[PDB]
């Protein structure tokens, strides 16, 4: 993750943040339309789950200058996800759906370079979580 | 089985399947320690026998939306089992041992919800096989 | 152990190792079928037991150029074995079953010359453990 990529994360976060509730909820709609059996793993109200996911994305942004410091957090997270029945193959699905939902809700406000930076950051977080 | 159970079977199979050889082999070790008398019935290499049992569990997953479609297959397999010396009381022994072995090998990666759904699917298969 | 036998141990271990989880669990199933009386000695989860056995076999391979260096390790392990109820006459049975299980899982992958070598290496380890 280079300096330009860090600043693209911060800039695009300023576009995602004020629309975070909508982007999270669109993400679950899009995810359950693309993989029609994964919704059973979600046992809590989806509005609550969406707040949790968007809070962690905001933590990644907040730590973007030193993702290394987020390694323990992400490891603990990744462990809990195995306990929910989440498997390694779910991560590319979730990443693609999240990035497409951000791109969908913001349109041109989410730039191609910003989406490339988020692809990398998600790929990092997924690697750390899946050990 | 209901829609949530069908989904749990499909999603949990994504963790059981890549570990299916180990889970099968663990299941024969566990079954032979729990009920040493049953081991005489197994006359073929256990490495090949585990492959066959795991192949049928994959078929149950592939067919899980319409287990009725599998009734004739399961009836033929139940008839063959009677030829091997298998009797009705062996089915609950085998289901307990198989479920325990998937729970052992996967630990908390086999969720309580998935275990309940697989418990039900095993019961259905054992019922069809024994008429 | 001569130079050629040492090489055969090292050669066959590159085939055994990637398969070690399955070979160790197949060994328990086969042991418990061949010798139903001994399963009562194995009181911990067999998935964890198999990991422990295959780890020590790795250590025997790692130290194959100087098995005399492993004498203390093997003495300590043999003492533990007495505390688990294991007696000398168990050793040939376990060795036979272990070798037959590696042969079964690898087939053609396990040559006669490699099986002979492992026979000698098992015999050395069992002699040391039984002092
Ligand atoms: C970087 C990727 C991800 C992040 C930041 C993330 C974030 C979160 C967070 C913050 C939680 C709340 C509970 C906890 O902290 O343990 C959660 C729960 C959960 N996540 Fe994720 N997640 C990610 C990937 C995934 C993937 C790939 C899936 C696959 C479907 C998934 C499915 C779930 C499920 C099923 C729950 C539990 C919902 C419940 O309470 O029933 N997550 N996730
Ligand atoms: C849902 C439950 C079961 C499934 C899916 C299943 C599956 C299989 C399959 C696929 C075979 C290969 C031969 C064939 O297709 O006829 C087989 C053979 C066998 N099964 Fe099962 N089985 C089940 C329950 C049982 C039970 C309850 C026992 C009681 C010990 C058992 C004992 C055996 C034996 C002895 C053989 C033959 C081994 C040999 O060839 O010598 N199975 N089983
Ligand atoms: C070269 C031969 C063997 C090796 C490398 C080996 C390795 C081990 C290892 C690493 C352990 C873990 C506990 C510890 O480290 O003290 C162990 C435990 C054990 N071994 Fe062996 N072993 C061998 C032979 C045997 C034989 C001949 C038996 C006879 C049945 C046997 C039965 C057991 C039992 C019952 C335990 C304890 C299981 C428990 O925790 O309940 N092992 N063996």
Image (spheres, coloured by chain):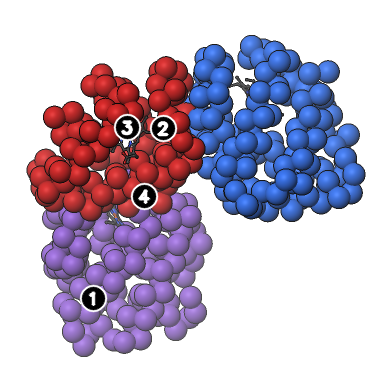
Chain colours: A purple, B red, C blue
Secondary structure of the residue carrying numbered label 1: helix
Q: Earlier in the sequence, mark 3 or mark 4?
A: 4
Query: Which residue position holds label 3?
Result: B99
Please, is residue A53 above or below residue A8 in the view?
above
State if disc 3 and disc 1 touch (CB < 8 Å). Answer: no
Q: Based on the displayed image, in which of its 4 quarters is residue B94 positioned?
A: top left
Please, is residue A71 above or below residue B109 in the view?
below
Q: Earlier in the sequence, mark 2 or mark 4?
A: 4
* Other residues around mark 2 within 10 Å, as few (<14) / some (14–19) / many (≥20): many
- Report in which chain the residue with disc 4 lies: B
Nearer the camera: disc 4 or disc 1: 4
Q: Is residue B6 visible?
A: no
Q: Which mark is drawn over residue B17? A: 4
Query: Which residue position holds label 2?
Result: B27
Q: Is residue A3 visible?
A: yes
- Report in which chain the residue with disc 3 lies: B
Nearer the camera: disc 2 or disc 3: 2
Question: At 71% across and 15% down in the image, what residue appears?
Answer: C89
- Report in which chain the residue with disc 1 lies: A
x, y percent for residue B43: 45, 31
Query: Which residue position holds label 1?
Result: A100
- The residues bearing labels 1 and 3 have C-alpha atoms spaced at a distance of 39 Å
């Amino acid at each position: 993750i280079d300096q330009k990529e860090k600043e693209l994360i911060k800039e695009s976060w300023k576009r995602i943040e004020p629309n975070k509730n909508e982007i999270g909820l669109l993400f679950y709609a899009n995810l359950f339309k693309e993989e029609p059996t994964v919704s059973v793993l979600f046992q809590n109200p989806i509005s609550s789950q969406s707040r949790k996911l968007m809070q962690v994305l905001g933590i990644l942004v907040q730590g973007i200058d030193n993702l290394e410091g987020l390694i323990p957090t992400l490891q603990d997270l990744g462990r809990r996800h195995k306990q929910y029945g989440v498997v390694d193959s779910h991560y590319p699905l979730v990443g693609d759906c999240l990035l497409k939902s951000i791109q969908e809700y913001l349109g041109q406000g989410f730039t191609e370079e910003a989406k490339a930076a988020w692809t990398k950051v998600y790929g990092i977080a997924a690697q750390v979580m899946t050990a």
